[PDB]
Image (cartoon, rainbow, N blue to C red; front, top):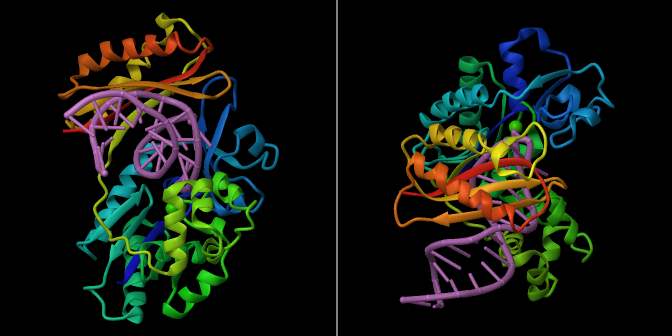
Length: 341
DNA sequence: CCCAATACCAGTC
DNA sequence: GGACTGGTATTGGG
Ligand SMILES: [Ca+2]
Ligand SMILES: [Ca+2]
């Protein structure tokens, strides 16, 4: 199999830079502002000038400003980044039938039918980078390899504005010499628990008692890392199909009183429904974040689709349920729809 | 046997 | 989490 992975570089920041040419060469930090005290919020993404000084995705805005007091800080404009992204995914589609959109800024393509070898794939990758650059002024990184997992790794190695092939010889090599925390689907929490068993490389997952690795990171990530280590990871590129749609808003001030919490809850419902796109969900979960940032939720599944009005009344009852099984106050309230018809 | 339905948990931008 | 979306570990039945 020949897999071509496409990953847009510092995407949210780069779109901001393309729309606003007076930001290029400056450190740029795209932020999600919570609207509570000023500068309350996290960093969604920052460009590569800003990453050099340690401003990265996930850190609080106030923390970022402890490093780059004079970076440009911009409100996340998700809907804008989504238009651009959609247009770029359409470009990719002219290159292959078999395409898997993995997120707002990555797609895997199966080009086995379109090319005969890795050298032809490289030449297609370049074709793609230039198409995207010409039509959208967006730089991307490309990875090419035997499967999805290693196509992505190849991209994580060549970013930004890069392209890399990991051939059959380097795959064996990489299975030996490559930190396990650079393995897609392995974050701090998993890269942590594995760091205390000695397991520091993929290959290490083969010397440990299975049941122990299992009893350590679950039967999913074990079989996953093992299959990667045996070099027998075989997942096909398939169309991804959104399985849920939701909205979770931060409220002005905390609360534990049902009356202020709507709208948004109610705003969250109306916003989600416009994102539903005449998709009809059969399940609904009301989602609450308390004071200490812990997540509590209650849900219900109907034998039929949920109308917009039904969502309203059923979420209040789901809201009330939460209210009297957790005494603490609500910082953020939202809703989540799933099991579509 | 699933698996469905129910939540709390993990990776990503 | 921000704010999303999947994953994931219980459970309750057929
Ligand atoms: Ca990406
Ligand atoms: Ca990116």
